[PDB]
Image (cartoon, rainbow, N blue to C red; front, top):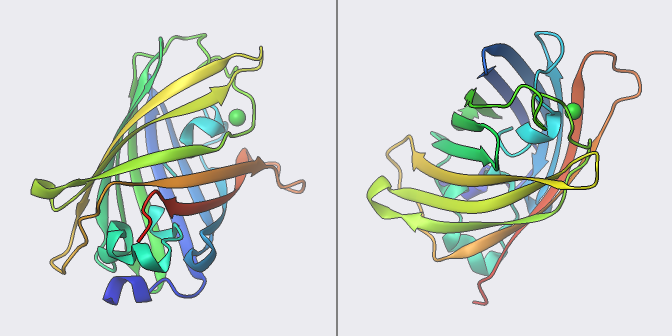
Length: 227
Ligand SMILES: [Cl-]
């Protein structure tokens, strides 16, 4: 198909986010590349407004599921690539248990040969010295499964899933995710059977970088369908 063929090689990625969490306004710019053949992502993010006012891990899911590796026998279930190049809207509510919430609206699409993720993020209801605004989350990331379903009247997909962020005392901060994607363009898009994405994510720092930043290496395989 048109859209899948755009991903057979290494694709440059740009991420741009504007955020407001409890009145803390901030922006992040990221760059890197994806190789969907291997389900592989590398991205470096820099907070361009100074210190990021929330923990970096909390923004990982918001900062391009078109880079998931869909096995050949599952190609007919890959909504994300099918929407390309015109792209998709991706909306979420991320509910931090016993704390505030993020609501995100993003558009993921090509600009030339570069895959771009532009995001608006709004966070409200955060506790001033909860785990988020108090910066009590460890700089690491657990592996998760993302459960996707068709959303046919949207001509798209949905997902609800749980992210657990380790807290510095050894506990975990749950971040419930509810997600809806909608194609932007007029080409045919794939409405998948139920399946999941299996994700691992590793966070690191660039030893040479003194701006507030995050390096992310992530591998994603679609799974849960046999034929
Ligand atoms: Cl952090």
